[PDB]
Amino acid sequence: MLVAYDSMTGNVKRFIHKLNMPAVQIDEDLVIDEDFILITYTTGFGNVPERVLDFLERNNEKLKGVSASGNRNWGDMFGASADKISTKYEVPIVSKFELSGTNNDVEYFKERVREIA
Ligand SMILES: Cc1cc2nc3c(=O)[nH]c(=O)nc-3n(C[C@H](O)[C@H](O)[C@H](O)COP(=O)(O)O)c2cc1C
Ligand SMILES: C[As](C)(=O)[O-]
Ligand SMILES: [Zn+2]
Ligand SMILES: [Zn+2]
Ligand SMILES: [Zn+2]
Ligand SMILES: [Zn+2]
């Protein structure tokens, strides 16, 4: 299962390297031609980062689920980028995790993708 991701300060990037799954960094010409899971971080007041919004405008056809990195100090805004993407594109929230994730977060992601794929 291909994982598409973006990371500003490296936490999501660290997480996707722990997964050892096929993974691609988002950019403005990337076109994904296969089912994929998105991993995003959360920015500002519960928001999806602009680069991720731009990518999804072009590539949502094959989106099968979303995970978010965030921080529980945001309370009910924790991982709210995933809530927004799930609600809009009608795909499941695979998982939410803090920062670069724990080993349990890594294993849970993989188990959940195996269920969804
Ligand atoms: C300005 C600011 C706003 C943030 N907004 C949220 C938020 O609304 N919800 C959340 O769960 N985390 C929020 N975060 C936490 C980041 O999503 C978290 O640090 C994430 O691991 C960053 O991923 P990256 O290192 O891959 O860029 C915020 C962080 C910053 C610095
Ligand atoms: C080439 As990579 C897995 O660091 O996005
Ligand atoms: Zn790498
Ligand atoms: Zn834009
Ligand atoms: Zn736009
Ligand atoms: Zn709130």
Image: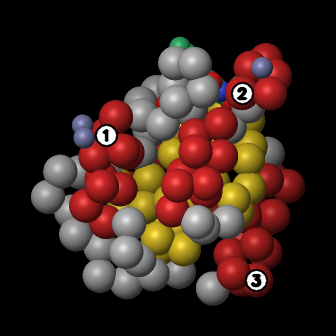
Quick check: marks 2 and 3 in contact, CB under 8 Å? no
Q: Which residue is mark 1?
A: 51
Mark 2, secondary structure of its residue? helix
- The residue positioned 60% from the left and 67% from the top of the image is 91
Q: Is mark 2 within 8 Å of ligand 1?
A: yes
Image: 33 above or below 11: below
Question: Which amino acid type is marked by label 3?
Answer: Glu
Mark toward the viewer: 2 or 1: 2
- The residue positioned 52% from the left and 30% from the top of the image is 47
For marks 2 and 1, give the CA distance: 20 Å
Question: Which amino acid type is marked by label 1?
Answer: Arg
For marks 2 and 3, give the CA distance: 26 Å
Q: How many numbered marks, from 0 up?
A: 3
For marks 3 and 1, give the CA distance: 28 Å
Q: Which residue is mark 3?
A: 115
Q: Residue 68 versus residue 101: which sits nearer the camera?
A: 68
Q: Is mark 3 within 8 Å of ligand 2?
A: no
> Is residue 14 shown to the viewer in this render?
no
Q: Which residue is mark 2?
A: 77
Q: Residues within 10 Å of mark 2 (few under 14, many from 20)?
A: some
State ligand 1's quadrant: top right
Q: Residue 43 versus residue 14: which sits nearer the camera?
A: 43
- The residue positioned 67% from the left and 66% from the top of the image is 92
- The residue positioned 58% from the left and 66% from the top of the image is 90
